[PDB]
Image (cartoon, coloured by chain):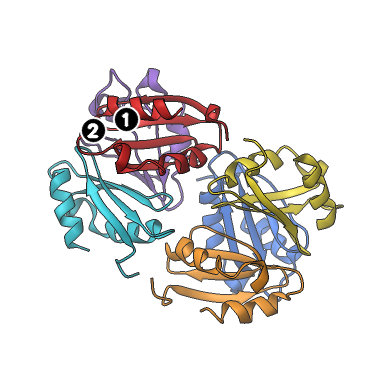
Chain colours: A purple, B red, C cyan, D yellow, E orange, F blue
């Protein structure tokens, strides 16, 4: 489960986009689950090797790209 | 699948997120698909128990979180 | 894989949103995955049969739209 | 999640098959998981709205079909 | 949505198994969905690019193979 | 990626049933996807925390159980 499964992070005006080794998704996404709104995550969606993630109120897409790039 | 399978509903600049009792996500998702552009629901995608819905042009997030929150 | 399966393609101030025929999302979502960050594809999370895709920093939602419509 | 989201229950010589209402698969799926091997469930895989469920190993399919049937 | 997508069809003494060009999985799945109990299918479950489909009793998996092939 | 994501492995007559830590479902089935009829995995449909894999012709569920065990 080592996060070498992570193949790319990125973020725009709306959401943070982590891409993964074919089949990570739900594992890498299960991880971000620990962060919650308090740690800057409003929600999270997985899908194939694509995971979105829009920041909670009080955090910016960047605030997010940061503390997440942090838990990685 | 009582609305009460909905653990929460918050939003942000881009999307209105719902969080469900494990596995209910898509059942609630199927409910949103009943509204569509009609009610300013341009699109909606479910994951684990995290919904990601987004407003139609001429609609805002508060408007969404106002009409989904009204459906529940 | 004929793109008549794509019921809708439309957008908002946040992501392009394609509506496909029952169960076509995961397929159509394969094409959008081909474009990559090179064409402004920041991400594409598929779902039931609704596809959420968003613009790589540098492009606009409105500029990804016209583009999908094109590589479609 | 009232068990009227199920539409039918059947079984052949290898799995119990629950065909449910749109997008309810995950939930009813969510229920059977509480009856691990001990009550006869070696495994269960949910879907679109169909559910495969197979017997532990001391329970014929018929054994499982019944237990399930009782469980709802 | 052309049946050029179906990359494989063989069966064992339990379920028939369709293999595809990744993605179709779901689309392909939903077509079989037209056969029903009556045409010999008790159910179907799919995902990535594999479709499992088991015969309704009174049908031998062999008898399903010839029926799915009679769609495909 | 590590195989300590597999929470158990059992089987019977039809399909082998491998469980896993939350999310791990998909990833682990990958290793599997790299088995082929050659080794005896006729197909593997997995989802959530259960991977069902079935044996190809000429391989007992036990013999395939074997396969996963060595490959695992």
The vertical placement of D15 against A37, above or below, is below
Q: Earlier in the sequence, mark 2 or mark 1?
A: 2
Tell me the SS state at disc 2.
loop
In the image, B60 versus B23, the foreground residue is B60
Left or right of F26, for residue F66: right
Whether residue A2 is visible to the viewer of this picture, yes or no, is: no
The answer to whether tags 2 and 1 share a subunit is yes
Q: Are marks 2 and 1 in contact (CB under 8 Å)?
A: yes
Q: Residue A10 in the image: state x and y as whole percent.
A: 26, 39
In the image, C43 versus D48, the foreground residue is D48
- Mark 2, residue position: B59
Q: Chain of mark 1?
A: B
- Mark 1, residue position: B64
Tell me the SS state at disc 1.
helix
In the image, C22 versus D63, the foreground residue is C22
Left or right of A11, for residue B25: right
């Amino acid at each position: 489960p080592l996060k070498n499964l992570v193949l790319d992070i990125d973020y725009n005006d709306a959401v943070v986009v982590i891409h993964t080794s074919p089949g990570a998704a739900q594992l890498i996404a299960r991880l971000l689950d620990s962060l919650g709104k308090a740690e800057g995550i409003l929600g999270t969606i997985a899908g194939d090797d694509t995971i979105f993630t829009t920041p909670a109120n009080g955090f910016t897409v960047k605030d997010l790209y940061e503390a997440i790039l942090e838990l990685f």
